[PDB]
Amino acid sequence: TKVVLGQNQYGKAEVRLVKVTRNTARHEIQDLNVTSQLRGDFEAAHTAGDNAHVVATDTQKNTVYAFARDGFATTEEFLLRLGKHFTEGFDWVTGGRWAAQQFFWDRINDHDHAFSRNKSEVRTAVLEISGSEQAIVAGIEGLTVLKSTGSEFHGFPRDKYTTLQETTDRILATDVSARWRYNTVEVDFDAVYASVRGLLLKAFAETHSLALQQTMYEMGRAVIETHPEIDEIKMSLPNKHHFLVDLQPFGQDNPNEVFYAADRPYGLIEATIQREGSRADHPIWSN
Amino acid sequence: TKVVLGQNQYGKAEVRLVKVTRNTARHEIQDLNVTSQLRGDFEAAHTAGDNAHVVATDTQKNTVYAFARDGFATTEEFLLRLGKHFTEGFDWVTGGRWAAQQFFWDRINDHDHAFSRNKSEVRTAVLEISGSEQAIVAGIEGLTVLKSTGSEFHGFPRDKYTTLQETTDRILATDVSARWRYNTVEVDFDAVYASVRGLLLKAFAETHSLALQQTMYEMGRAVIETHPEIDEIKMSLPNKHHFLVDLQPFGQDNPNEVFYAADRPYGLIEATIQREGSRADHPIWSN
Amino acid sequence: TKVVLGQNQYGKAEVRLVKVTRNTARHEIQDLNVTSQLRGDFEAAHTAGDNAHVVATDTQKNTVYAFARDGFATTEEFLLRLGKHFTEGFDWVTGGRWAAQQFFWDRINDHDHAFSRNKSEVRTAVLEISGSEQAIVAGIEGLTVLKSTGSEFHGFPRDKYTTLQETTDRILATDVSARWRYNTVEVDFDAVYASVRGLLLKAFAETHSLALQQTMYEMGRAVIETHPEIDEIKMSLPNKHHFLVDLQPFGQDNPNEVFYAADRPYGLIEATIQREGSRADHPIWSN
Amino acid sequence: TKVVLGQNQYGKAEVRLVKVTRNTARHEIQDLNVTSQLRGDFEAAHTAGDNAHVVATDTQKNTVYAFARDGFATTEEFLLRLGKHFTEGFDWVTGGRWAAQQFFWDRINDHDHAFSRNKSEVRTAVLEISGSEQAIVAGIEGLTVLKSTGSEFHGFPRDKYTTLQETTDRILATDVSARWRYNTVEVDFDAVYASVRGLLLKAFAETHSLALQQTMYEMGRAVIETHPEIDEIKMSLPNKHHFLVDLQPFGQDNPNEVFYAADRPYGLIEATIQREGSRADHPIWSN
Ligand SMILES: O=c1[nH]c(=O)c2nn[nH]c2[nH]1
Ligand SMILES: O=c1[nH]c(=O)c2nn[nH]c2[nH]1
Ligand SMILES: O=c1[nH]c(=O)c2nn[nH]c2[nH]1
Ligand SMILES: O=c1[nH]c(=O)c2nn[nH]c2[nH]1
């Protein structure tokens, strides 16, 4: 009967940007996929078609490239400039969400302006501004890792639908997807990302696993303990199954050597590892 | 300081199920992509690696196939059965999230047991249980639509970054991605899905659009006004830009006929249309 | 010692074109993904960097839109016009390959200028010109089909590595990818495409299958037998495995009802069905 | 006219294999995506549904895992064993096509049994046996490269549809996809792959490009000149357009710094660089 406009946001999504730094003969590359969305009073825009407040998505796009011209130290700095620009520049704009993916490049044999793409991981950054407060969630994804041993899984409940055999030696493979919320913008974003990444890899590799849930916890723990600027870290880890193939039918044995890597289904272990006391329901996770 | 385990869930994702109903010569096909994750007391599993509370992801998988044997009338019904089984079947399991995608099939010339997949859209359903609380969200996705005319965009702000030219005749294309929350479990899930689908399509086509935002408001308004069982509908619509090519350099005009369909970037207009007085932020939207 | 430039071709790939026909209120849509590549004398371009013979890929792109202004009856007519233009327009250009994917759209409730995308199949066309001769291969792909019964596979040899069990009732699912070469350009492209599509569906559905190889064969024979303008048809059909799940461990039987749809690996059955006495090594299949 | 069965092949595609070598504490990882198809007399299987000659695809799959148990020095060596097995093992099987994608892994901090995926490239191998002949084509793909300068494109023809402007400084970006055919199986497969790779990257980075065509020619020539065992190298290089954004409308210049990385369309420059007098139509290039 009575309809009302609820939460809403709009902008330009996936603006691919490449910024070359060449004031010297030693060129640098910054490759981003930027998304800009504004929040505020767009009541008339939706219910009436009154675009008076609608800052064109096309215009948000231009702004991205226009700002890019000036250069940026980090992806987070670039995003902070955009968010500040749209919120302060417009009355009806009370905040928004600004995200970006960062793609890495490696010099080809230390060449000054020749590079090859490093596709082993993708860095993420998300800025959400709400009136007077703002927040930044950095992250990493697409980083596949695997232990060929040093992992077991047993002691789990056995109901009438349970057929999984316990084991003390299996492969543990997953795709590292983690995002951590900063409790301050005053952060050396590049140094932290590098450190967090190292901590994640280290924890995953050195922890004798009794379960993916356990490994993820240790991973989240190493980060929280190391960076005070980080309140919480959320991770989503798929248990990419590697089934030890049965070779007895062929007169052979399989001493944990030959595996079949199945695509689907896969186990999905997810959890938030937070700092005691820190918030437990930040609006930035609402997306 | 002190590290703590916050929110967390685990289970089996993307279990591909195909249920054939063949008690009669007229076979029926049900195609699903099912994901099952449990919520509860998994503290020890994460902190100490004690899996006494860890119902194997493999077991959740086996349960889906086992329960499929008995058949099911609707996707939502199927998910409801799994949710209650796990929550009730284990005391440390206080809830969870069970979602699925439903893929459609059409008979090959009305053949009794020969079909071809209809890929024009994908139906979704998500069930979330929190103690005694049960919430279901159904939706549609991958349904691309386009208006060759009956769409305009003008009256928007113009700053030093605005280049977009006002227009009273342009193409409006998008991928319909919608999800609505049911306020009751007693719903004719299939009838309502078809209805809502028709309402979204009808509103998209018939509304003389003055902005994607307006078309979306009308699409949702139609849904709420028609279905008492729905408290809100969320839509994420990309403005898939079709650029009218400039052929004047070659001496030809382009009477809104020849277009270049860009991939990225694209505008992304999102909004929530709800029944007045309905809950503002149900937890199911957090996932 | 002596390095040589062999086969080569270049151009613009994936030019997304949308042509709206609106001489009346009843609008029509033509959606294409065009790829144009030229062949001829480009020796100097590769060996010396002399671009005098290089009709820019950008130019080929502009040419697609420019020609699009005049409209076209079919996708094949459009490709024929392009190839002709590039081969006759440039002395050193002696040939090329012009391909296109055609995307289908359906009217939203018979609306005059609002449509929804039909993603159940994709039509393709390829034109190859070599000197004074030209050949056209049309096709369909992405059309997924499945028989819930009417399929068996037994009588295969057995060796020490064989474990597959015989069957007289299984699911037979595949993705229809078919490409047929015309032996003349004087063809009703649209009607033949609709016909072939129909013949492939009917043969797949009605043939009681003793193997995917046998089914694919009947599908090809029907095409060759029905259309004189077709010298040969090639098909690539994956055997999309649907494993009848073993429910015995859970105290249940599975009367051919519950299946697991595995992604990989999959059987891949391919063959060429030709008219007796027709070329078997046509260049168009090489590229 | 009468219908006939032309060229044909069948087998199991994309069998995902992971071979862990753990005779010592220093584990090794081989990760492949294998496809095996057979060629020979399968007339009866297609025309009659007589499967006596049909070595089950499931069986081909089993053989892959069984052979993997014995380990293999290289991907090529692995395909050769499979190929000889099926051709020599069955009188009616006269040949076939075996292919594989090899995925790379790097140790985590030189850890003995923990690794992370190097997704920056994918190695490929294809074996085709025709009687006693064994043809091997090795290749690389997914290797994205870019030059921020040292690339120009001018001197091209300006026909009635040419608007592209001449330039002496632009970004040159592509996805290195290359495949080279060995004239002998007596090859240190791993060493040549590393060399070839090095050669392709070097020629790309170090050549002052006057056109993608020129760059590609030098890449291929360096390979043909360096390795006597390679008869030819084919390359398919997309010109991934990075458009220098026009910021003048915003009162700023853009000294080759701010770019827009467009997805489609894109230039596609392909060519074959061979040893003078070598075969130019090897069957292996048709699949
Ligand atoms: O690490 C694991 N966690 C789980 O929850 C699980 N279920 N099956 N195997 C498993 N492995
Ligand atoms: O419908 C539209 N809404 C927007 O917000 C927008 N921005 N540019 N074009 C647009 N079109
Ligand atoms: O390197 C290039 N080769 C081409 O053929 C071309 N066409 N446009 N730009 C181009 N760049
Ligand atoms: O139809 C089939 N064809 C084959 O070649 C095969 N191999 N295993 N199962 C099979 N089924």
Image (cartoon, coloured by chain):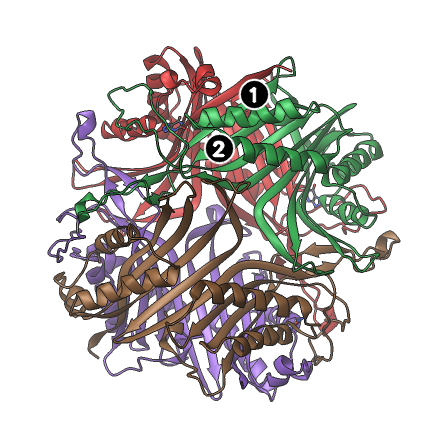
Chain colours: A green, B red, C purple, D brown
Task: Give a yes or no on whether discs 1 and 2 share a subunit.
Answer: yes
**Disc 1 residue type?**
Thr
Compared with B97, D151 (above or below) is: below
What is the chain letter for disc 1? Answer: A
Q: Is residue C127 visible?
A: yes
The disc at residue A1 is: 1
Near-viewer residue (A169 or A165) = A169
Residue B262 rendering spot, x and y as whole percentages: 62, 55
Q: Residue at x 83, y 32 (%)?
A: A88
Among numbered discs 1 and 2, the one appearing first in the sequence: 1
Q: Quadrant of residue D88?
A: bottom left
Task: Check mark 2 vs ligand 1: CB closer than 8 Å? yes or no.
Answer: no
Picture coordinates of residue A239, whole percent (x, y): 42, 34
Name the outermost residue toward the front.
D24
Does residue D170 lie above or below A56 as drawn? below
Q: Give above or below for A12 relative to B67.
A: below
The amino acid type of the residue labelled 2 equals Leu
Identify the residue under disc 2.
A237
**Ligand 2: which quarter?**
top right
> Quick check: D119 above or below B40?
below
Q: Position of residue B51 (x, y in %)?
A: 38, 19
